[PDB]
Length: 11
Image (cartoon, rainbow, N blue to C red; front, top):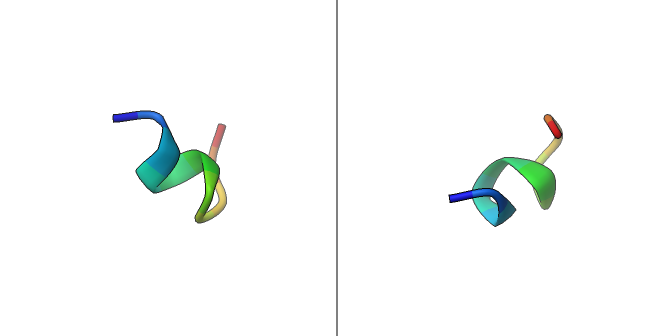
């Protein structure tokens, strides 16, 4: 949801 991009490198 949020984690799959936040704990990768987006927002």
